[PDB]
Image 1 (cartoon, each protein chain N blue to C red):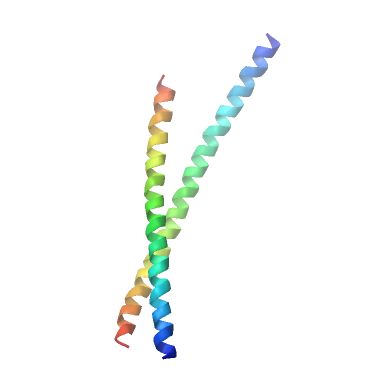
Image 2 (image 1 turned 90 degrees about the vertical axis):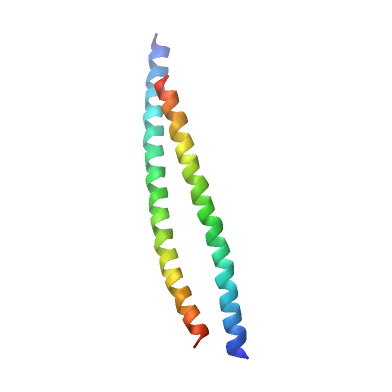
Length: 56
Length: 48
């Protein structure tokens, strides 16, 4: 009985940890996507600048 | 000719980093596919 209780508690702890880790990794992926979006926006602005500089 | 070669390499690395950004975008897309598939399979597991 003692061993079973220990195992059950370990399982609950690990499950909660996996839930937190999944949420955190999803949030960090969202943040990386946002920063990539900003980089792409300024890169397209610079590409337009280069297109005009082709006439420069 | 310095300006010419420099603008040439400028447009060149433009194109290269652009391909890399396309690859990274496709990576993000398959990543969101992975998020959705993990979400649905996790939800199925949790339902059962």
